[PDB]
Every structure is written in structure tokens, then in C-alpha cells.
Image 1: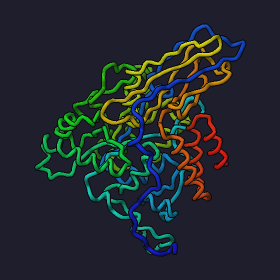
Image 2 (image 1 turned 30 degrees about the vertical axis):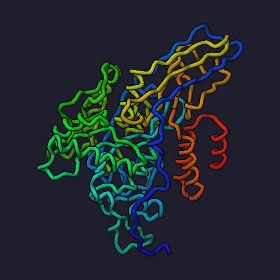
Image 3 (image 1 turned 90 degrees about the vertical axis):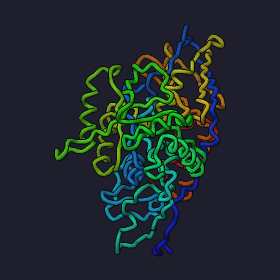
Image 4 (image 1 turned 120 degrees about the vertical axis):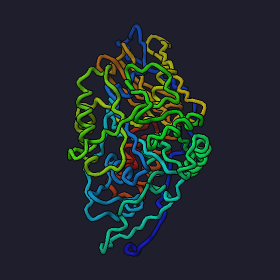
Length: 460
């Protein structure tokens, strides 16, 4: 019975097994060349930004907001949107949608530079030690007497956040749930692991390794720096301003500057108006002198949805494709690999070269974004007879870029299985056009294989 009220705990049927991700990746890629396209010499690098992007946009949405799901995530991933309401996951799964619902008709993405979509990524803070994350969702298809079930909640329910994990949304600590008098450096230190245990229990044993500083409260940063699982941090003051082409240090336990770009009081401008103006200013500089556009957000709304679309249309897939729009954790990991991994290429015989690269994250937890770009100078797509890879590579996309050759290499261990999970969801919901687009998007991340061919057949 569709029409009957139900109050449910939002749940998703699978979550990427983050706990199982391997820490160490050994990449071996064998490039076989055409007979009359023998090359004398190849050399390699990991470029400054993933996908050979020119500049970096980082986004962390604070306060574990309902709109992180209903507006930010929904707009990026081609999902149903409202102008004034807030869907939970269970609304989308049941098709119980608010009465003003619309959709943009596209996802919001860049490309990877080798012909695939890369949807915008971002981080949300988590109130993991707050029992309000356990709130139920009222689902009731066809009930129009009111829309109270779609009102803004004080924060995300766990199910919303679990689902977002399947799309590579990142996580960060923020406020911890202690009385205000107890928010001393030592007491905050002791509470980090308590929140961490809930994060791990709920998010398939993902370890959170970021703090987004709340309230300008430096006790949080002082405490976080004594908790070794936190590897990266952000704040508005007491931070380093990231210039991605200049930055030379270790950034382990470095507080990276972020800004909210508040509009001047009574000016009728919005935070997105101010961020838009800041981007335009920054883009006038040569890419090497540009700062990262590193934003915080609180509640997101229609204005933010339009802004995200503007980014897709101006600097993403539907514009110049010059931006890397990502979360700080993914960026941190990539910087780490760029600093510490050393790609090599060795000639095996006259027409065969072997590319090798070890990806090893830090000791605390795994890295969850083990994907890199490798550029090969002196090679073109047209020279290549075939490319083969080892088992550690699960996604592989390649092609020409400027006068050289680029490979996008994903080493997420369970990526094929994850892609198959989206295929199964589509198979259980074959009239949902969004479910089909998600299956296609994830299956397209896979390297050429028997499994990829099988999954492609299932989603024709």
C-alpha cells in the first residue's frame, strides 16, 4: 500500500567497502606500439592537478546540513530538486517527491580529459556523535494535505550521508557533541575517537581524516593536531593559502585556508555572487600564480544550484573544462602521491614500454581516492597498438593532451563491484532514468575487461 504513511530510517542498499580499501597500489601498465611508430625515448610525470586541469576549486559544506544532500549532492548528481523543500534518500527511492520538484536535466561535471565525465566532488562535515543523525523520514506517496515530511531537518540523517559516500563525497569533523564548558583542548582530543567510532560504524568503516574548524575555535585545531588520524584541516584564519603550482612542502597536518565569501551587510548579494566575482578575479592570472578557490558553505539553496550549474557551464564539461572541482581529502591524497610516488617508464623491447608507479598512502588509514594522472612525453595515441594493465588498476582512461599523452589511472580495489552495485540498482528500478545514468557513469570508470563488457550489456 503506496498511500500509507511510513516512518523509516533512511538506508541505502550498499556502501563502498572503505574499510577494505588497500593502502598500497603497484601500477604496471604495458604500452605496445605499432610497427612503424617506434619511439626513441619516453619520460613521465604526475601533473600538478589531476586530469591536467589548470586550477582547483575545493568545497566543504559545514554543519552537517540537510541541504548537503537535498541541494548540493542532488544538483551535482542529476537528482530531483526542490526550490523550497528538502528530500531525504527514502523520498527519492520511493518517488515521494515534493510538489515543486524539478530537475536540471544534466549532471554537473568536468571531463577527465580523456573523454569521461567526472562529477563535481565536495566534502560535508558530520555530527557523528549527535543522536539527531538518527531521525526518521516520513514517506507517503500521494499525500498532498501537507508537505511537512519535506521540511528542513536540523542535520543530515545517516542514510543520506551513507548514500553520498557511494559518489565519493568526503567527510570532515566539525563541532563535537560535548557541553560548551567541556570544549577544552584535552576534552575535545578525547572526543575525536568517540565520533570516529560512529563514523566507522555507519560509513562501512571509512576513517575520517579531516577537521573543518568550527566557530573560529582554535582549541579544535590544537586538539585535532594531537589526534593522528586527522591528516588535513581547514579554517578561515591560522591557515596557509594554497597555491597549487607553488606549494612545495609536506602538507601533513597543515591547515589549508578556506573562505565563505560573505556578502556585505544589506548589499543584496549572495555568497555565490561573491565566489563568482572572486573566481573571475583569480582567472586573470596565469594558472601557476593562481590560488585555489577554497570555499566553505552552510545552507545551500536554489542560488547555490544555479551557481554550480554556472561552474559546469563556464569551467566544467559544458564550458572550457579547465577546473578540478573536488574535495580537500581527494586533493590532499593526490598531492601526497605527487610528492612521494615516482612514475617510471622502461623500454621492454623495440615496440614495448612498461610504466610503473607505486601509490602508498600514509600510515593512519587507507587513502580513499587512489587515482592519478600520468603524462607520457614523446608518445601519442596514434602510436599505440594496445595498452594492458595489472590487477591493481581498476579504472583506465587515456588519450592525447596538448603535444603529449595522458593516462587517468584508478586503483580503487572494489571499483568493479561498486559499478556492478549501481547496475543491480538500475536492474531493480529499470524505469528510473537517473539510476540508468548512474550505472552508465560508474561502469564507464572501469578499465576494458570481461566484467565491463558484461555490465555494459546489462545496461543497454
